[PDB]
Image (cartoon, rainbow, N blue to C red; front, side):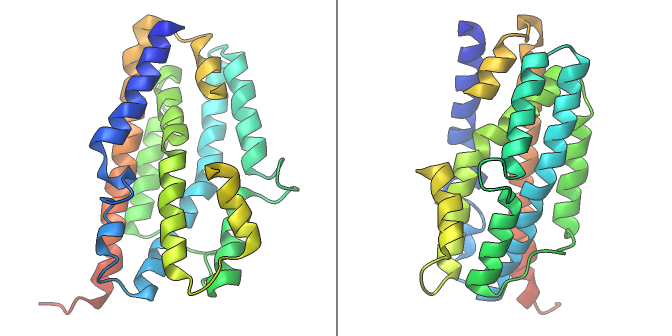
Length: 230
């Protein structure tokens, strides 16, 4: 209803105003592009790729939290998200695979079997700690994934275009266009009570904070490869 709609609009605005990681100009990797080598930005993309993979499992944890609380409509919406990320609208090919295959075909950058870096491992541990809380908080963090999706994908398009000398592979271009050229919010609205809006907001905040910290740390990891110990 109106009060939850106000909250979700607010959280989207918060993200747009206050978070440089989701800015197409102020993201810390974008800010290092003048000085960065191909290898360094390829490293960022290898690490980045881990996150969409792992987010399917986190969405599963949120689905289970929703079921556990009797938020059945939300569990159903989350199942549809999982099905889509695992390929239900892209011929059975997961979104992760489209990205990974596209990076390999376009750049010769292998990302499958990438181990998380210190920063990425820290992100994944932090995120799990959020997805282990009560349903309202967990769904806030889950809504943060949805809210960050478009700004994130816009940054990824930029970095991938920066890396490519020519056109990007056509399947990868479709992956991007399908995302960039309401269901979760409306489902949660049916169950969430006003007394838990604060917990939903807290989960959202915690997730976007964790993701921002990761982008910052991953920019430092990338640039540090040419540092001479001093």
